[PDB]
Image (tube, coloured by chain):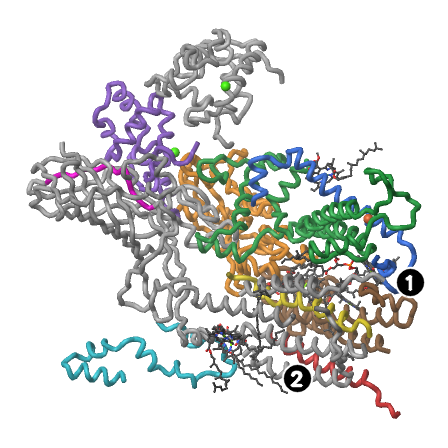
Chain colours: A cyan, B orange, C blue, D purple, F red, G green, H yellow, J brown
Amino acid sequence: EIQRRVDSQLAEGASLSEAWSTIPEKLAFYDYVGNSPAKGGLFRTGAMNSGDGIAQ
Amino acid sequence: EIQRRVDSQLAEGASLSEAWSTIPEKLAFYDYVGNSPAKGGLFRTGAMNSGDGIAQEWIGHPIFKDKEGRELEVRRMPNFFETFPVIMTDADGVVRADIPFRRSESKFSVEQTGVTVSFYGGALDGQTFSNPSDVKKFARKAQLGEGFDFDTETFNSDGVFRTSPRGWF
Amino acid sequence: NFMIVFQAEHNILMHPFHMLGVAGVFGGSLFSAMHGSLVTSSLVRETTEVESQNYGYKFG
Amino acid sequence: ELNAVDAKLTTDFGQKIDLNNSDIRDFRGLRGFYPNLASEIIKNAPYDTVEEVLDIPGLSETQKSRLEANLGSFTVTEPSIELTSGDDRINPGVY
Amino acid sequence: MESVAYILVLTMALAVLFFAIAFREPPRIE
Amino acid sequence: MESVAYILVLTMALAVLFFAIAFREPPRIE
Amino acid sequence: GIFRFILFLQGFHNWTLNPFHMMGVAGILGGALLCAIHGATVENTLFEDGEDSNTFRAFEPTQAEETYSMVTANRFWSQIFGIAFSNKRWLHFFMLFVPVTGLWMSSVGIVGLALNLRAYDFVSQELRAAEDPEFETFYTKNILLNEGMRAWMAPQDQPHENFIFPEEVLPRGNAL
Amino acid sequence: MQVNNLGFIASILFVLVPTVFLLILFIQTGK
Amino acid sequence: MQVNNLGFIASILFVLVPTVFLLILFIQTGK
Amino acid sequence: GLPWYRVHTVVLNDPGRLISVHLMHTALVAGWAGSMALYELAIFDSSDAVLNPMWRQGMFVLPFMARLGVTSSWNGWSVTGETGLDPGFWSFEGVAAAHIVLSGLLFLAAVW
Amino acid sequence: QGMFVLPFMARLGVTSSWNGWSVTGETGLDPGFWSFEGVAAAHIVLSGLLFLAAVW
Amino acid sequence: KSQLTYDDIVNTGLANVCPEISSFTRGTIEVEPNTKYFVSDFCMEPQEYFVKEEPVNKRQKAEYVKGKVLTRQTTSLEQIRGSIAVGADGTLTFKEKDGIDFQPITVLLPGGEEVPFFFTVKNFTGTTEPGFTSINSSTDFVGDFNVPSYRGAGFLDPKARGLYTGYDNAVALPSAADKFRTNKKETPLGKGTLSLQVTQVDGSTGEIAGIFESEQPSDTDLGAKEPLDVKVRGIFYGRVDTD
Amino acid sequence: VELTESTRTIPLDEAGGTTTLTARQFTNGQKIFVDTCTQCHLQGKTKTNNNVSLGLADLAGAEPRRDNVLALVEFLKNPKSYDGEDDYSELHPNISRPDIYPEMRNYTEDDIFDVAGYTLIAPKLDERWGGTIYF
Amino acid sequence: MDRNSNPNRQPVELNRTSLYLGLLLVAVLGILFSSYFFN
Ligand code: CLA
Ligand code: CLA
Ligand code: CLA
Ligand code: CLA
Ligand code: CLA
Ligand code: CLA
Ligand SMILES: CCCCCCCCCCCCCCCC(=O)OC[C@H](COP(=O)(O)OC[C@@H](O)CO)OC(=O)CCCCCCCCCCCCCCC
Ligand SMILES: CC1=C(/C=C/C(C)=C/C=C/C(C)=C/C=C/C=C(C)/C=C/C=C(C)/C=C/C2=C(C)CCCC2(C)C)C(C)(C)CCC1
Ligand SMILES: CC1=C(/C=C/C(C)=C/C=C/C(C)=C/C=C/C=C(C)/C=C/C=C(C)/C=C/C2=C(C)CCCC2(C)C)C(C)(C)CCC1
Ligand SMILES: [Ca+2]
Ligand SMILES: [Ca+2]
Ligand SMILES: [Fe+2]
C-alpha cells in the first residue's frame, strides 16, 4: 500500500522526497516487523513498548 | 587526633600540603558524620553505601579564608540535626560568614565576604576555589566533616544516611 | 500538620482545657487498665488451665 | 551555580546601596532618606551612573544636598528583574 | 504500583469488617 | 538475588522429600 | 519541661510519623474510648433493683447477680455498631490489653529514637520533591515545619552548644 | 515514585503469613 | 543479572498460595 | 482447646519434647548464623578495606567472626586488608559451613 | 501499551475518557457518563450488587 | 456592570464581566493629528484559552487545544488606565499604563495537565497602521507586552528553595544536596503579543469595545520546565477621554 | 545586677547631654509604655510599620536623631516622618492632638519624659528590642 | 424468611500422602517456572 501511494505521487510528478513525505507515519508504523504479533515470547511480558521502546 | 598529627608535622617544618598529605584516608574517613551511627533512620534500610554511596577518595582538608585573611571554621552538623545552617566562624568564635536564607538583608554571605577555600592533601590537594558556588558547596561538605568522593551509581544510593551495624545491633 | 500549626498559633499545650483532655485520655486509659485488670484478677475459677478462662463466662 | 541574586551579592550590590536594585529599607541608614528621598530615588530609577541620581526631575535643594553628601554610599548595577518585579523594592515581604 | 498495595490492604480491612458484621457468631443465651 | 529464590524452591522440594520419607503415613494391614 | 520534650521530639525526630507512636496513640485513645463506653453501657443497662431515682443505692457488693443486663447491652451495641461484646471476661481483658499494648509499642518507638533511628522521612516523596518543584503533600509541609522548629529553637534549647545562627540563616516563609 | 524495591513483597508477606496462620487455626478448629 | 522485576514475587506467590491451600486442607482434615 | 498463645505449653511437662523443641530452636539459630554468614560472604566487597570496610556494607555477622580471630576467606582475602593468607578450614566459609552442618545435626537430634 | 480491555470498550462505541481524551486521537469530546471510567465504575458497582445477591 | 450597586453585584460573577456599550453603536472618535488621549477604565475579559501541545514526534503541527479554567471568575483585567497617541502620519498607539493588569489563571487540558499562566497586559504597546484620523471599527492595535514570571522571586518551592530566599540545594538529601537542577531558580521575563480589534465605538460617551487575541507563555515554575504557548481570546472595553 | 544608675543613665540631648532616670521615673515610664505604646510597640517593634522600629539603630537613624530623651519628647509632641519631612500628628499618637488621641490627654510632661527614658533604657535590657516582627 | 441449616454440606479431606504429593508438585512447578518468571 505504501509503495502504491508513493508511485501514484511519482506518477503525478512529485519528487522522491515529496512522494515519500506524503506517507503517514501511522501507515509506515504498521509496516514494521516489531508490530507483528508473531515476534514475541511467552515470557517476554508486558507492553510492546517494553521491547523496542516507545516509537517517536 | 587528625589535627594533632597535622600540627606535629607542621612543628617539624612540613608545609600545609605535606602535613595534611600525611593523614591516612582511613583516619579522615572516621571523621565524617555519615559514618556516625546516630544519623540513620528506622526505615532507611541496608548498608550505609546505600546512602551516601561507596566512598572513593578523600578530597583533602579545606581551609576557608575570607576576603580579609581571616581563616574560618565551618560549624559541623551535630548528631541531632537532620539539617543545619552553614556558619563560618573565625578563631575567636565570631561568625564571619554564612549562607543566608533571606538575601535582602544578608550581610555575611559567602558572596559578600569573599570567602575562598584551598585544599590540602587528598584529591584536591593544592587547589583553591573562589567561585562562590564552589565555596558554598565545599562549605556544605565541610559541615559533614572530612569530604569524600562517592560512587552513588552502584547501589543507586539515595542520598540519606543509614545507620551502621553498631546502631542496628 | 493541623496539630503542629494549632500549637504554633494557639499554644494548645499550655491551654488548661487541653490539659484536662490529656488527663481525660491518660486517666481513661489508666482506669480502663485498672478496671480490666482487677476484674481479670478476680475471675471466679470456672475453667481449666488448658482452655481460655474466657469460656468461664456464659452469655446471659 | 548561583541563581541571579547571589551573583548580584558577589558584585558591588552586596557592598553598598544600589540605586537600581536596593530595597527602600536599605536607604534607612542614610539620615534624611527614608522614606521620601528613598521613594523618589526608587521611582526615578534606573540610573546609568550614580551621578544622575542628582538629575532626578523635580528635586529639592535640601534633597539635592543630601544626595551629594551620600553619593559615596551609592552604586549602579544592571537592573535585575528579580529584585524589581512586583514592587519588591518597596515591600519584598520583610517586616 | 505501591498504590495497588495500599488499596489491597484497605480493601482487606473493609472486607473483614463486612464479614465480622454480616457473618458473625450469633450471641446465644444458654 | 534470584539465586535466593532458586535455592529456596530447591530446598523446599528436598525438605518435602525428607518428611515424606521420615514422616510418612505407615502402611497398615487391616 | 515535658511540653518542651514533646515538641523537641516532633521537631528533631518527627515522632508523630513514627508508626510505634501511632500504635501508642491508638492504644491510649482506645483505652479512653473503652473506659467511656463501658461505663456508659453499664450505667444505662442497669437492672431496676431499687425504688429510688438514685440508682447507686440498688447495688450490694456481696450480691451474686449481675447488676446490669449483658443481654440488653449486647443487643444494643449489635444493632448500633454492628458488633458487640458477648463475653464479660473478654471485655475486661480487652480493656486491660488495649492501653497496655499501646504503652509498650510507644516505648519500643522511643527506644528507636534514643539511637536517632527515626521514622523521619519517606524517601520516595523526598526525591520526587527534590526533582519536581510542584509536588507537595502534607508530609513535605510537616518536614518544613520541623526544619523551622529546629533552627529557631536549638540556640535556646541547647545553650551548652553555643549555637550562633545569624538572623539571615533562619528559615522562614514570606512576610513572616 | 521511587519506592523501596522490597516494599511490595514485604507488605504482601507481612499480611499473608499471619492471615494464613489464622485461617489454618480457624478452619481446623473442632477437629 | 537484570532479571524481570516481578520474578521474586511471582515465584513466592506461585509456591506459597497452593502450599497454604494444601496446608489448610490437610490440617483441618478429621474435623 | 488451647488458645493459640498457649500452644507451646504442651511441652511444659514433657522433658523429652522440651529437649526436642530446644534442639530445634538451637538448630534454627545455628542455621541462621550459617546462612547469614553465607549471604554476607556472597555480597561482601573485600577489595577496599579502607573506604569500604565491612561496617559500610551492612555486614552484621562478619564482625563477630572477626572479633574472635576468623578474619580470612578461602577466596584469598582477609578483612585486615591483606591477601594470600591461608586460614585453613576456619575461614568465614568454613565457619558458616560448620554452622550449617551443626544446624542439620541438631535438627536430627530434635527429631529423635 | 499492552491494553487488553480498552480495545473491547472501544469496539462497541466507548472511545472517550472523562479526562478529555479519546482513543481516536481527538480531545475535548464529551462522552457523558459512558466513558472508560464510567464503564469501569459500572462494572465495579455491578460486581458489588452481584456479590450481595450471591450472599442472599 | 449596568447601573446597580455592589450589593446587586456581589456573588453573581458580574464583577468579572467587562462592561458593554450598546447595540445601535457605529460611531467613531475623531482624533487630533498629534495629541494623546487618556483611556480611563480599560477592561479585558478572557473567554477562550488554548494551549499549544508539544508533540514528541517532530516537525509536526502542534494544534492549540482548548483548556478549561479551574480558577473561578477571577479572570479579567480591569480599571486599567492608559493612553492613545496619534502619530505624525496618523498612526494610533495604545499604551497600557497601569491598573489590575494581571490575573493568574489555571486551565485544565485534556489529559489532566494543568497550565498556570500569568494572563496580563503589562506595559502593552500596540499600534495601528498609519492614516488613522479616527478610532473606529477598523482600529486594530497590534503590539507587545511583558509577561513577568508567574512565581515571584520570593516564592518558596515545597522544599523551601527560592530565588532571593530559601535554600539553594536539596537539604533533605545531604549527600546529594547539590545534585538537582531545580536547586537554581530563575524568573525570566517573557514576551507576549496582543491584538485589540476595536469593533464598536460610542464617540459621544467615548466608549470603545472590541475583541482581543493574545499569545504568551505559561508558567515555567521558576524555570523548572519549558513554557507552553497560551492563546487567549476575549473581549475588551474602555473609555477614551476626548477632551 | 540591679537596675543601676548607669543603666538608667541615658542621653538627654544631642550635645552630649545625659540624664539619669530614678527607679520611680523608670517604673512610670514602663507603666505608660505598657498601657499606651505596647499595642503598637511591643518589644520595640512597630506593628503598623516595622521599617521604623523603636530600636537604637532606628532611633538614631531618624532626622534628627531620636536616640536622646529630648528628641523623643519632641516626637511625642509633634510626630514627623523618619526623615523629618512630613507631619505625622494626624497619624501618630501625640499630646498635641487630644481631640483625636484621647488616650493621651491625661499625660503630663513628666509622663512623656518618663516614657522617652524608658524607650531609651529598654533596648539595652533586651537584645530582641526593635528586631523583626517574628524574632 | 428463616435461616435453615443446609443439609448438603460435606467435609473435605486431604490425607497426608496427598499433602506430600501436592507439596512436591508445587515445589517442582516453582523450580520449573521460576527461571522463566525471572527471565
Ligand atoms: C486471557 C485473558 C488475558 C489476556 C489475553 C491478557 C493479556 C495481557 N495482559 Mg492481562 N490479566 C488477566 C488476563 C489476560 N490478560 C487477568 C485474569 C489478570 C488479573 C491477574 C490480568 C492482569 C494484568 C496485569 C497487571 C497486566 C496485564 C498485562 C497484559 C498484557 C501483557 C501480557 C503478558 O505478558 O502476560 C504474560 C503471560 C505469561 C507469563 C504466561 C503464564 C503461563 C503460566 C505460568 C502457566 C501456568 C502453568 C500451570 C501451573 C501448569 C499446571 C501444571 C499441570 C500439572 C496442570 C497482555 C495484552 C500487562 C500490561 O501490559 O497491562 C497494560 C500488565 O501489566 N494483565
Ligand atoms: C537483632 C538482629 C539483627 C540485627 C541487629 C541486624 C542488622 C542488620 N541487618 Mg539483618 N537479619 C536478621 C537479624 C538482624 N539484622 C534476621 C533474623 C534475618 C533473617 C530474615 C536477617 C537478614 C538480613 C538481610 C537479608 C539483610 C540484613 C541486613 C542488615 C543490615 C541492615 C539493617 C536493616 O535495614 O534492617 C531494617 C529494620 C527495620 C525495617 C525494622 C523493622 C521493624 C518491624 C517492622 C517491627 C514489627 C512491628 C510489629 C509487628 C508490631 C507488633 C504489634 C503489637 C500489637 C505486638 C543491618 C546491619 C541487610 C544488609 O545490609 O546485609 C548486608 C540485608 O540485606 N539482614
Ligand atoms: C513521671 C512521669 C510523669 C508524671 C508524674 C506526669 C504527671 C502529669 N502529667 Mg505528664 N507526661 C509524661 C510523664 C509524666 N507526667 C510523659 C512521658 C509524657 C509524654 C512525653 C507526658 C505528657 C503529658 C501531657 C501532654 C500532659 C501531661 C499532664 C500531666 C499532669 C496530669 C496527669 C494526669 O491526669 O494523667 C492521668 C492520671 C490519673 C488520672 C491518675 C491521677 C494521677 C495523680 C497525679 C497522682 C497523684 C496522687 C497524689 C496527689 C500524690 C500525693 C500522695 C497523697 C497520699 C497525698 C500530671 C501532673 C497534663 C498537664 O500538664 O497538667 C497540667 C498534660 O496536658 N503529661
Ligand atoms: C526464652 C524466652 C521465652 C520462652 C521459652 C517463653 C515460653 C512461653 N511463653 Mg513467653 N514471653 C517471653 C519469652 C519467652 N516465653 C517474652 C520476652 C515475652 C514478652 C514479649 C513473653 C510473654 C508471654 C505471654 C503473654 C505468654 C507467654 C506464654 C508462653 C508459653 C506458651 C508460648 C506459646 O505457645 O506461644 C505461641 C506463639 C505463637 C503461636 C505465635 C507467636 C508469634 C510471635 C508474636 C512472633 C514470632 C516472631 C519470631 C518467630 C520469633 C523471633 C523472636 C526471637 C528473636 C526472640 C511458653 C511456656 C503464654 C503462656 O503463659 O501460656 C500459659 C502467654 O500467654 N509469654
Ligand atoms: C562449638 C560450637 C560453636 C563455635 C566454636 C561457634 C563459634 C562462633 N559462633 Mg556460634 N553457635 C553455636 C555453636 C558454635 N559457635 C550453636 C550451637 C548455635 C545455636 C545457638 C550458634 C549460633 C550462633 C549465632 C546466632 C552466631 C554465632 C556466631 C559465632 C561466631 C562468633 C561467636 C561469638 O561472638 O560468641 C558470643 C557468645 C557470647 C558473648 C556468650 C554469652 C554467654 C553469656 C555471657 C554467659 C551466660 C551466663 C552464664 C552462663 C552464667 C554465669 C556463668 C559464669 C560464672 C561462668 C563464632 C565463629 C556469630 C557469627 O559470627 O555468625 C556467623 C553469630 O551471630 N553462633
Ligand atoms: C448490561 C450489562 C452490561 C453491559 C452494557 C456491559 C458492557 C461491556 N462489557 Mg461487560 N459484564 C457484565 C455486564 C455488562 N457489560 C456482567 C454481568 C459481567 C460478568 C460476567 C461482565 C463481564 C465483562 C468482561 C470480562 C468484559 C466485559 C467487557 C464489556 C465491554 C465490551 C463488551 C463486549 O465485548 O462484549 C462481548 C460479548 C459477546 C461477544 C457475547 C458472546 C455471547 C455468545 C456469542 C452467545 C452465546 C450463544 C447463544 C447464547 C446461543 C445462541 C442464541 C442465538 C440464536 C440468539 C462493554 C462496555 C469487556 C471490557 O471492555 O472490560 C472493561 C470485558 O473484557 N464485561
Ligand atoms: C452501623 C452498623 C455498621 C457498622 C460499620 C462499622 C464497622 C464496625 C464493626 C466492627 C468490626 C469488627 C472488628 C472486630 C472483629 C469482631 O468481630 O469482634 C467481635 C467481638 C465480640 O466479642 P465477644 O465478646 O463475642 O468475644 C469473646 C470471645 O469470642 C473472645 O474471642 O467484639 C470485640 O471484640 C470488640 C473489640 C474490637 C472492636 C474492633 C473495632 C474496630 C473498628 C474498625 C477498625 C478498622 C477500620 C480500618 C479502616 C480501613
Ligand atoms: C522477620 C523479621 C524478624 C525475624 C526473623 C527471623 C526470626 C527469622 C529468621 C530466620 C531463621 C531461623 C533462618 C534459618 C535458617 C536456616 C537454614 C538455612 C538451615 C539449614 C540447614 C541444612 C542445610 C541442614 C542440612 C542437614 C540436615 C537437615 C541433616 C543432615 C545434615 C545436613 C547438613 C545435610 C525480626 C524479628 C528479626 C525483625 C525483622 C523482621
Ligand atoms: C493468576 C493467573 C491467571 C488467573 C487470574 C485470575 C483468574 C485472576 C483474577 C482475578 C479477579 C477475579 C479479580 C477481581 C476483582 C475484583 C474487584 C476489584 C471487585 C470489587 C468490588 C467492589 C468494590 C464492590 C463493592 C460493593 C459491594 C461489596 C456491595 C455494595 C456495592 C459496592 C459497589 C459498594 C491466569 C489463568 C489468567 C494466567 C496468568 C496467571
Ligand atoms: Ca534589602
Ligand atoms: Ca490603647
Ligand atoms: Fe466492668
Q: Say which residue label 2 marks.
A: N28
Q: Chain of mark 2?
A: N
- Taking the magenta stretch, the answer to whether it contains residue L83 is yes
The local secondary structure at tag 1 comes to loop
Residue found at x 17% / y 79%: A15
Q: Which mark is residue J73?
A: none
Question: Which quadrant is the C terminus of chain C positioned in?
Answer: bottom right
What are the residue bounds of the magenta stretch? Answer: L75-86
The image quarter in which residue G81 lies: bottom right
Look at label 2 and name its amino acid: Val
Q: Is residue M104 left or right of residue F29?
A: left
Task: Name the image quarter holding the N terminus of chain C.
Answer: top right
Residue L50 screen position, x and y as percent: 30, 56
* Left or right placement of residue B77 versus residue K1 in this view: right
G150 and C15: which is toward the camera: C15
Can you give x and y, in whole percent of width and height, for residue L171 in the image? 50, 49
Q: Nearer the viewer, mark 1 or mark 2?
A: 1
**Residue tagged 1:** C48
Task: Name the residue: 53% across, 13% down.
Answer: M29
In this rendering, do the residues under marks 1 and 2 share a single chain?
no
Chain letter belonging to callout 1: C
In front of the other: M124 or L17: L17
Q: Is residue J62 visible in the rendered structure shown here?
A: no
Q: Quadrant of residue L152?
A: top left
Question: Among all residues in the image, which is located at the extreme front?
Answer: N1
Whether residue L64 is visible: yes
